[PDB]
């Protein structure tokens, strides 16, 4: 993270479920103890069903994403929808290449028809992993035990949701950097759906 | 920071014979207190009845020795398989070494 | 038309042809003759070394690019020297990068594709030499012919340059014999000896006229000149 | 192949000539007659606005006489565009030279500067030269007033007076006739104007058909002063010639 | 590939001529007759909007284009050539002037700058001169209104008024007839209408014709308020309405 | 970017561009130089096609590359300038690099390649200038006379002329000059020069311009008066018979 | 005028590039070769002309593979397509390097067509003297493509190039009618073999060798591979019977 | 016109082919490789008495152990000469030794084809072939003395002796008979110098010709006019016997 | 001299024949295509010709989707089409990338036209002998029609067609549009607009068309797409009803 840019952190988690994957992250962006923008969406679309959880330097992610979005769009404008995996490959490249200049972790997730939902983590190492679910950002620290014990495959949409909803709330609860509101994004064959949650709810779970 | 260098351990000994010549070092390769390979031949004939060994960070000398024999090949190409004089290689290798001067 | 279509490497004939190539291909014939053949165990290079004069020496038509690999040439020498060196690197490169003796076939591809640049690329010219190349490898002995068109071919035997056709027939005429000759390079030689004699027209090969090279199973790519060829003269 | 299309600019005549240079010179014949004179006390610059008209705006218009520096201004014989290139460059070059030494460029240095630049196209590049030649009017410390010239070939000379464009030989004759070394600017002024009016290919020699300038160390001075005359001023001095 | 035409494409004739330029002029003369007039209060330029098909939407093509809020341009010739030059002209103005001086260049320099480009086409290899000439009008603080004409020669000079393209000769003829110093723009506007009407063959109206002026600054067009120093663009383009309005005033 | 090869072997193996450059050389106003016993003198005809020029500010057909070494030429005044230039850099370079000004030959050989390069250089034409090089080596008074030509070839001359008509005056010089006796006196060397000069110049003093290199960076150009005085004298001795 | 053909990028008076059209000449001259997209996948069939006994059987191989799923074959000057092929091999590598996937046939198809067309874009660039039949199984089925020096390729239910293409195009058209269903790779293998011999009847004057390769979503899983041995020998005699 | 790398309809390079013309236009230059040494001699060919033949050297020393002579357009070689000399030095710089005459020679001929306009496959920047041919004489431990004829073709051969330049072929024929391995440096001097005087338009002298040798002991050694004049006069005596 | 024919430089008349010859290669593929702004939408109709069975017909298109929003149909050599489309496709994303929003249609055309203009002026570059047709529903302009030539010249169109018989189709619509007086079709459903065009396509071509016969594409708000043969046939169904 460079000196003077806003720090993301918050808590990003993406979980595949029986009908697909849903992405969620806190809304809170901070520079030090100061919360730069509490409402900021960290969930981002590079591509129609292909999406990303942005952690690390917001500038990086913000900058990186469109680049991927660019190429994918270009790629799609050529060859159509890439695999959510292929999308990850794009990030990895820039990540793995510019890692020395880049501080970003990225959970890449996209809904494929054939693959249903998918999740791909790219930590700052530029490595890539397809996962049933993934978490990253600062608050992710607190929730691993929670997540793992509580995670299941092919849960419902909503089972995942609350599993998400609780997990983040913990991170939001425990992490300072995690907070604002819980933005969730739905990835299925049904389509893309953003979901928001206000503290007065998820703070209480 | 990544260190470009290290040591693989193992001392080498040259001796010029009057009529003959001999060179030797151990076969032991190590890292710190860990033995890389008890048997790791460190000394190499490069051809023309001329043998070479580089003791230090191996991969350096390794690629070097490699590069050197490479030079030998082209020498024979260009000098029409003339034998390379033991001194010449030195003058040559000096360049190779000094080619890395910095 | 000629001056129109023969001028530039980049320009097809109305029939879609490259006369510069065809001319470059011509110089092959202008070049002296060299001969080559292989067993499965061995591959033989046989060249007739041409002079300017008797006061001059006989230009060597044969080149070693490697221990398993070297070549012969009929055509403009420098191109080969360019290519041979280029090739030598590759073999050495393969030897460097992969610790791998360059596959004779895989070797030809590069040169095939290399001159192919000259072909389609304006400003240049194809190489002025057709090439015979032998190598022994994990796939064994191999004889590869090159064309300045880029076209490469793996043969049992062949010859190029001036009037190489006679032996070429004789080789084809002799086909199954030498290829069966295995571990006896001598006959493999003496076959090629009789071969190059076929397209010998003006004179007989001599100690200096003839040039011989061989790679084989345990035979590294090597060259026999003069006294070496004497017993085979 | 590209060869078909090359005019092969820089290639020698069998006689060792460069026809482009030749032809560039030829277009310069077609260029508006431009004249300059080094007087004893100054240097005069007068050139015919060529291809003029009523709604042609004169005042802002300068197609010929351009100022590289306050000690170096020039008259242009050739394509207006091409010179402006060199014009700009030289200025920079001078400015550089100035910025280099904090001192003004001895004119030839700037002249020879452009000289070889033209010559740049001459000996290389397959590039057409400029169809332009120049009257180089400059004052220096060393030779004081200096009147130079150039040709697209880059060859260049000094002059006590000179003319370019059309009617040069005629002017040159008139000039090489009427000139005398000690002439004062104002004499040379009319002298050119005389030569101009005569060498004028049109009917009348008129200000609106002219560009005019002078390099002069003024009476109150120590700053050798270049001046371009305004059309009226030109028209005014046009009268002073009796040409009226 | 690898352009091997590095050699100047247009070469001096045995007569000392540059034919491409001459032919450009030829093509330029072929251009749709287009005019400009520098009046007292300002400058106006005009040209006929050429429809090669009514299916085509004329307005989608602009032969007159603002270079700077006080400078806009028009041509006679190949549209495409005019098109790209506009951008460069626009760009170089920002870059080589505004991005240096923070403002919009005096009409001359930009013109001088533009012509520089066209010259380059004439000289550098691999390229041909452009198929247009340019009538350029601008107002600057010190030189006020000015009107320029740039050729594929890259030569440029001011005018009191002028026209380029086919009927331009006939136009300029009538222009010289009509023009005086003291013409105010509107009459000059009206004049241009009169003049271009002659160069006009098919329908003559704001939908057939393209008019714009260098006028007084237009705070409305400034797009914002609160800045005293900037009262907006002097340039404007005229509506077919306004045109046809004054085409009544014919 | 323009590589195009102008200089090419003719069907019979010539480069006409070179051969045509020879013409501009011939077309170039004649230039001549001769080396006196201690000295060298350089005659040049001022291109006389025009006049009324200011000769002061107009450069001399002869030019100094370095304090001890000068050059004259015949050909396009343009082409010279570049040639003139790099040599000047060269000496300074040699001065700087070698702690020493060049030998006349050194720059000579240097300049030659420059031409000689542009021959087998592509995308450029050769120069149209042949040159005469004069100078006395560092710590050597000895006359050094060198003739170069767009083909980039140089050589030493007891005396040499170049340009138009050079053959004519050369024939004069060939007989008029004697190797066994260099015109030791600068003047007589100058004299022999001007004698040779009017053989072409066709009666002018100003039309003629003279320059003399003496040892140790001693180099001088001569005034028309000095010239005319020789012109006068020469005429007499001719007239006398 | 004339000689429009004499430089590549030039438009003919009718707006054509005869060089490419001339390049097309040797394309026909190129050894007749065909390709077939069977039900799951594609098959690549080419005649190998035997010039002499000195040729070593099976050794000089025409059909070339790009990545592991894409075979390619071309009538024309061998080094050309080879040169091109490498670039394709480059393309997919880059593509896969970027996209982590093996490249879609159509994707791969497109990239080349540009690079070929590039050689239509300059009078100094010699068009390609080859036309490659190429394809393979990809994410969605297979595809069968043949790219022309024109820079034009298409989806092909069947494809043929070289001399005997007519005899081929005949047979291909037939099997289309024989099997609008599709075809089994096996029969795709078999039928091509017949087609080749039939196609060879144009070149019947000399003996040849038969090389056939294929990419089967089923049998090669989507890899591209040669037909070899018995199955190879099968289609031979299958055809060698049917040829009689 | 026509491309520079354009092959003859026979597959030959016109410019190269034409380059051979100026080769014959070059002064006749001759040398003889002996076991004793290699004699070199060349045609000064002064175009004027005012031309001082001292400044004419078509014989040049590459190095002590290796030197060469030129016949053709001379200053072309300057690069090559400068190039060549470098290589040996370079070789010695790397290899702490002399270079095989061939190895050097071979290296030099690689300059040959490097003319081209943006040539396909490499960047070799020169417009035209070299306008000169080279007799090359050097003594190397391996090959002893040798004589190679460098060519703008990039081809070169060993030669018992060789005649290049204008009167080459006839002089060459002379060499054919005259030469034998057992020739002596002095004889070779005599032979060359005579055959020079033979082929020379002008009456041979030390001034209108130039001599030198390369001798394993002394490497490359020039002959001065005086030793030359003696040999000349010596020939004049020996040439006049019967 | 006469190379002016061969290269791009002003004729003695100031003309570029390479350009004008490139205008030949336009209809060389001999496809009569059209474009019309519907009410909300824009529809492109074109001849889809399949000479050979062995082809994949589905692979045959001159209508290319440049963006999510912008489709483009091409008239001329398929390689240049395959060439040009990518160029465009490169732009929009980069435009979208650089400028944050998808390139409005004209800009593309304006952009692409420059290239030709470049090729126009550049010698070693030949121009492409394709005419390009750019339509989409521009959020600001709604339906929009832009057609570029090898000259770098282009303009908006109320509607336009391209092909050998383009002239007639031009007339037909002009008549129709003069009759309508309105720039775009009143029909809200492109469906009708498709059928409308095909009608006037069939009309001005006097030629009936099957599902395979036609290449069809549909510019909609925020999306361009091309119809199936079914959709085609579906339209072919109703046209058989009204007519």
Image (cartoon, grey):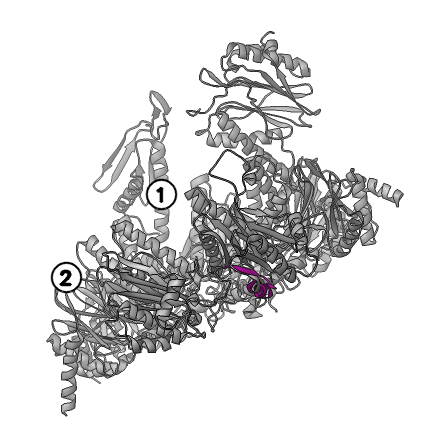
Callout 2: residue from which chain?
Answer: F
Q: Quadrant of residue I138?
A: top right
Q: Is residue I30 above or below residue F141?
A: above
In this rendering, would A105 be left or right of H208?
right
Q: Quadrant of residue B13?
A: top left
Which residue is label 1 attached to?
B69
Q: Residue furthest bottom?
A: F241
| Magenta-colored stretch includes residue E173 | yes
In the structure shown, which secondary structural element does the residue marked by tag 1 occupy? helix
Residue G21 seen from this side: no
Foreground residue among A146 and F238: F238
Foreground residue among H8 and B45: H8
Write down the region rendered in magenta. E159-176
Residue A36: mark: none
How packed is label 2: few (under 14 Cα within 10 Å), some, or many (20 or more)?
Answer: some
Which residue is label 2 attached to?
F138
Q: Residue I68, position in %: x, y?
A: 66, 37
Q: Residue F230, position in %: x, y?
A: 15, 80
In this rendering, would D209 be left or right of E74?
left
In this rendering, would A82 be left or right of B96?
right
Callout 1: residue from which chain?
Answer: B
Q: Are marks 1 and 2 on the same chain?
A: no
Q: How many marks?
A: 2
């Amino acid at each position: 993270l460079k000196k003077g840019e806003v720090s993301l952190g918050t808590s990003i988690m993406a979980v595949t479920f029986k009908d697909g994957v849903i992405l969620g992250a806190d809304s809170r962006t901070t520079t030090g103890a100061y919360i730069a923008n509490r409402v900021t969406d960290k969930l981002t679309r590079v591509h129609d069903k292909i999406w990303c959880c942005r952690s690390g330097s917001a500038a990086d992610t913000q900058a990186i994403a469109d680049i991927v979005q660019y190429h994918l769009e270009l790629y799609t404008s050529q060859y159509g929808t890439p695999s959510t995996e292929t999308a990850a490959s794009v990030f990895k490249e820039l990540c793995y290449e510019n890692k020395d200049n880049l501080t970003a972790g990225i959970i890449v997730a996209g809904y494929d028809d054939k693959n249903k939902g998918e999740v791909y983590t790219i930590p700052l190492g530029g490595s890539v992993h397809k996962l049933p679910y993934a978490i990253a950002g600062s608050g992710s620290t607190f929730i691993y035990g929670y997540c793992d014990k509580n995670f299941r495959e092919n849960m419902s949409k909503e089972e995942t949701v609350d599993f998400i909803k609780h997990s983040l709330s913990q991170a939001i609860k425990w992490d300072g950097s995690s907070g604002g509101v819980i933005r969730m994004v739905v990835l299925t064959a049904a389509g893309v759906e953003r979901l928001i949650f206000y503290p007065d709810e998820y703070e209480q779970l | 920071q990544f260190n470009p260098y290290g040591d693989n351990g193992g001392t080498i000994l040259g001796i010029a014979g009057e009529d003959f010549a001999v060179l030797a070092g151990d076969t032991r390769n190590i890292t710190d207190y860990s033995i890389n390979s008890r048997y790791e031949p460190k000394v190499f004939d490069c051809g023309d009845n001329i043998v070479m060994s580089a003791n230090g960070f191996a991969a350096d000398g390794d690629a070097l020795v490699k590069r050197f024999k490479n030079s030998v090949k082209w020498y024979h190409f260009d000098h029409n398989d003339k034998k390379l004089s033991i001194n010449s290689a030195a003058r040559n290798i000096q360049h190779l070494l000094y080619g890395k001067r910095f | 038309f000629r001056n129109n279509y023969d001028g530039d490497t980049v320009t097809f004939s109305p029939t879609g042809r490259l006369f510069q190539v065809e001319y470059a291909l011509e110089a092959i014939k202008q070049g002296s003759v060299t001969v080559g053949l292989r067993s499965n165990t061995h591959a033989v290079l046989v060249a007739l070394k041409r002079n300017a004069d008797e006061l001059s020496s006989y230009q060597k038509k044969i080149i070693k690019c490697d221990e398993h690999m070297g070549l012969s040439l009929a055509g403009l020498a420098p191109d080969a020297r360019v290519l041979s060196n280029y090739l030598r690197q590759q073999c050495n490169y393969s030897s460097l990068v992969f610790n791998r003796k360059l596959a004779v076939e895989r070797a030809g591809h590069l040169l095939c594709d290399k001159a192919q640049k000259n072909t389609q690329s304006y400003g240049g010219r194809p190489y002025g030499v057709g090439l015979l190349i032998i190598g022994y490898d994990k796939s064994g002995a191999h004889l590869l012919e090159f064309q300045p068109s880029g076209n490469v071919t793996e043969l049992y035997g062949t010859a190029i340059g001036a009037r190489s056709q006679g032996a070429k027939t004789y080789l084809e005429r002799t086909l199954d014999t030498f290829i069966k000759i295995d571990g006896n390079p001598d006959e493999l030689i003496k076959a090629g000896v009789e071969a190059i004699s076929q397209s010998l027209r003006d004179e007989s090969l001599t100690v200096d006229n003839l040039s011989i090279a061989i790679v084989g199973k345990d035979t590294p790519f090597t060259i026999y000149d003069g006294e070496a060829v004497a017993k085979y003269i | 192949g590209s060869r078909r299309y090359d005019s092969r600019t820089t290639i020698f005549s069998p006689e060792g000539r460069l026809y482009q240079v030749e032809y560039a010179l030829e277009s310069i014949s077609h260029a508006g007659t431009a004249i300059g004179i080094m007087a004893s006390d100054g240097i005069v610059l007068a050139a015919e606005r060529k291809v003029t008209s009523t709604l042609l705006e004169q005042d802002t218009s300068t197609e010929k006489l351009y100022k590289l520096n306050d000690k170096i201004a020039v008259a242009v014989a050739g394509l207006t565009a091409d010179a402006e290139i060199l014009i700009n460059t030289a200025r920079i070059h001078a400015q550089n030279y100035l910025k280099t030494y904090n001192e003004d460029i001895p004119v030839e240095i700037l002249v020879r500067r452009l000289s070889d630049i033209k010559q740049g196209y001459t000996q290389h590049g397959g590039l057409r030269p400029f169809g332009v030649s120049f009257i180089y009017a400059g004052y220096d410390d060393r030779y004081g007033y200096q009147l130079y010239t150039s040709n697209p070939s880059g060859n260049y000379t000094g002059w006590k007076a000179i003319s370019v464009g059309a009617n040069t030989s005629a002017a040159q004759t008139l000039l090489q006739m009427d000139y005398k070394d000690d002439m004062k600017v104002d004499d040379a002024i009319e002298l050119a104007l005389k030569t101009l009016s005569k060498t004028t290919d049109s009917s009348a020699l008129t200000y609106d058909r002219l560009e005019f300038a002078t390099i002069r160390k003024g009476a109150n001075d120590g700053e050798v002063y270049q001046k371009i005359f305004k059309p009226q001023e030109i028209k005014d001095i046009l009268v002073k010639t009796g040409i009226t | 590939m690898t352009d091997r035409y590095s050699f100047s494409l247009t070469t001096f004739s045995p007569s000392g001529k540059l034919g491409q330029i001459d032919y450009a002029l030829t093509a330029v003369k072929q251009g749709v007759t287009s005019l400009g007039i520098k009046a007292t209060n300002g400058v106006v330029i005009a040209t006929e909007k050429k429809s090669s098909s009514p299916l085509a939407m004329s307005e989608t093509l602009s032969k007159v284009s603002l270079l700077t809020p006080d400078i806009g341009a028009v041509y006679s010739g190949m549209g495409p050539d005019y098109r790209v030059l506009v951008d460069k002209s626009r760009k170089v103005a920002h870059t080589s002037y505004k991005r240096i001086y923070g403002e919009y260049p005096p009409t001359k320099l930009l013109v001088s700058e533009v012509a520089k480009i066209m010259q380059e086409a004439t000289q550098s290899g691999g390229v041909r001169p452009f198929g247009v000439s340019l009538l350029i009008a601008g107002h600057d603080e010190f030189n006020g209104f000015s009107l320029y004409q740039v050729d594929p020669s890259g030569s440029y000079f001011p005018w009191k008024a002028t026209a380029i393209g086919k009927g331009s000769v006939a136009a300029k003829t009538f222009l010289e007839k009509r023009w005086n110093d003291e013409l105010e723009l509107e009459d000059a506007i009206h004049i241009a209408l009169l003049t271009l009407k002659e160069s006009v063959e098919g329908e003559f109206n704001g939908d057939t014709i393209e008019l714009a002026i260098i006028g007084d600054e237009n705070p409305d067009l400034l797009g914002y308020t609160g800045i005293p120093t900037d009262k907006g663009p002097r340039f404007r383009k005229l509506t077919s309405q306004e045109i046809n309005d004054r085409l009544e005033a014919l | 970017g323009y590589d195009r090869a102008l200089s090419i072997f003719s069907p019979d193996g010539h480069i006409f561009q070179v051969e045509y450059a020879l013409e501009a050389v011939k077309r170039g106003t004649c230039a001549v130089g001769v080396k006196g016993k201690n000295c060298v003198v350089l005659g040049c005809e001022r291109r006389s096609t025009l006049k009324l020029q200011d000769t002061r500010i107009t450069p001399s057909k002869v030019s100094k590359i370095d304090s001890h070494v000068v050059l004259s030429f015949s050909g396009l005044n343009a082409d010279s300038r570049i040639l003139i230039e790099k040599a000047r850099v060269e000496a300074q370079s040699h001065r700087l690099t070698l702690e020493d000004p060049v030998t006349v030959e050194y720059l000579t050989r240097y300049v030659a390649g420059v031409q000689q390069r542009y021959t087998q250089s592509g995308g450029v034409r050769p120069f149209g200038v042949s040159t005469l090089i004069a100078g006395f080596d560092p710590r050597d008074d000895e006359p050094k006379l060198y003739q170069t030509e767009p083909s980039g070839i140089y050589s030493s001359w007891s005396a040499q002329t170049i340009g138009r008509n050079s053959k004519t005056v050369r024939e004069f010089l060939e007989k008029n000059y004697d190797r066994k006796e260099p015109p030791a006196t600068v003047e007589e060397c100058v004299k022999l020069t001007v004698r040779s000069l009017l053989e072409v110049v066709q009666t002018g003093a100003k039309n003629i311009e003279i320059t003399v290199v003496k040892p140790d960076s001693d180099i001088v150009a001569l005034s028309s008066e000095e010239i005319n005085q020789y012109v006068t004298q020469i005429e007499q001795e001719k007239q006398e018979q | 005028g004339t000689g429009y053909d004499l430089s590549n990028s030039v438009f003919s008076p009718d707006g054509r590039n005869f060089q490419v059209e001339y390049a097309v000449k040797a394309v026909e001259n190129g050894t007749t070769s065909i390709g077939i997209k069977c039900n799951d996948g594609v098959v690549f069939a080419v005649e190998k002309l035997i010039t002499s006994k000195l040729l070593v059987p099976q050794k000089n191989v025409k059909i070339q593979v790009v990545d592991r799923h894409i075979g390619c074959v071309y009538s024309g000057l061998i080094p050309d397509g080879r040169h091109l092929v490498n670039r394709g091999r480059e393309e997919a590598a880059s593509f896969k390097k970027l996209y982590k996937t093996p490249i879609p046939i159509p994707a791969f198809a497109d990239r080349l067509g540009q690079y070929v067309q590039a050689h239509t874009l300059y009078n100094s660039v010699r068009p390609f003297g080859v036309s490659t039949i190429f394809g393979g199984v990809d994410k969605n089925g297979a595809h069968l493509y043949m790219l022309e020096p024109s820079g034009s390729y298409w989806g092909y239910k069947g494809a043929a190039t070289g001399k005997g293409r007519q005899s081929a195009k005949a047979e291909l058209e037939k099997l289309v009618d024989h099997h609008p269903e599709g075809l089994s790779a096996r029969e795709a293998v078999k039928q091509a073999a017949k087609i080749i011999y039939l196609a060879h009847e144009d070149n019947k004057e000399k003996d040849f060798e038969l090389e056939i390769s294929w990419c089967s979503l089923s049998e090669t899983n989507g890899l591209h591979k040669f037909v070899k041995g018995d199955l190879l020998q099968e289609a031979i005699d299958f055809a060698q019977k049917e040829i009689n | 016109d026509r491309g520079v790398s354009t092959f003859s309809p026979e597959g030959r390079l016109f410019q190269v082919e034409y380059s051979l013309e100026a080769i014959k236009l070059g002064s006749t230059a001759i040398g003889i490789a002996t076991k004793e040494g290699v004699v070199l001699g060349v045609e000064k060919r002064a175009t004027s008495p005012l031309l001082e033949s001292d400044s004419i050297e078509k014989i040049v020393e590459i190095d002590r152990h290796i030197g060469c002579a030129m016949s053709g357009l001379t200053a072309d070689a300057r690069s090559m000469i400068e190039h060549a000399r470098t290589a040996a030095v370079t070789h010695n710089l790397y290899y702490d030794e002399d270079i095989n005459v061939e190895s050097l020679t071979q290296s030099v001929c690689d300059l040959a084809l490097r003319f081209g306009e943006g040539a396909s496959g490499e960047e070799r920047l020169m417009s035209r072939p070299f306008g000169v041919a080279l007799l090359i004489a050097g003594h190397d431990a391996d090959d002893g003395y040798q004589l190679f004829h460098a060519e703008p073709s990039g081809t070169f051969y060993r030669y018992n002796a060789k005649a290049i330049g204008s009167g080459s072929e006839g002089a060459q024929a002379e060499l054919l008979n005259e030469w034998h391995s057992s020739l002596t440096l002095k004889e070779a001097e005599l032979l060359v110098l005579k055959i020079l005087k033979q082929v020379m338009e002008e009456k041979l002298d030390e001034n209108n010709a130039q001599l030198s040798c390369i001798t394993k002991q002394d490497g490359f050694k020039i002959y001065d006019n005086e030793k030359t004049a003696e040999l000349i006069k010596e020939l004049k005596e020996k040439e006049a016997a019967e | 001299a006469g190379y002016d024919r061969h290269i791009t430089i002003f004729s003695p008349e100031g003309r570029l024949y390479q350009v004008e010859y490139a205008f030949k290669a336009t209809n060389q593929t001999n496809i009569n295509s059209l474009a019309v702004r519907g009410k909300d939408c824009t529809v492109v109709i074109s001849q889809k010709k399949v000479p050979d069975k062995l082809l994949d017909p589905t692979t045959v298109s001159y209508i290319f989707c440049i963006s999510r929003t912008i489709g483009m149909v091409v008239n001329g050599p398929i390689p240049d089409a395959r060439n040009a489309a990518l160029r465009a496709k490169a732009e929009a994303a980069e435009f979208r990338y650089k400028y944050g929003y998808d390139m409005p249609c004209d800009v593309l055309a304006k952009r692409m036209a420059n290239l030709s203009q470049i090729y126009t002026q550049r010698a070693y570059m030949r121009p492409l002998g394709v005419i390009l047709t750019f339509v989409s529903v521009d959020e600001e302009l709604g339906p929009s029609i832009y057609k570029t030539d090898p000259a770098g010249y282009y303009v908006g169109y109320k509607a336009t067609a391209t092909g050998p018989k383009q002239q007639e189709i031009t007339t037909n619509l002009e008549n129709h549009f003069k009759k309508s007086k309105i720039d775009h079709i009143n029909e809200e459903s492109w469906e009708k607009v498709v059928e409308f065009a095909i009608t006037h396509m069939i009309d001005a071509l006097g030629t009936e068309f099957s599902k395979n016969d036609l290449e069809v594409g549909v510019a909609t708000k925020d999306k361009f797409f091309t119809l199936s043969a079914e959709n085609i046939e579906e339209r072919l169904v109703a046209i058989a009803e009204q007519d």
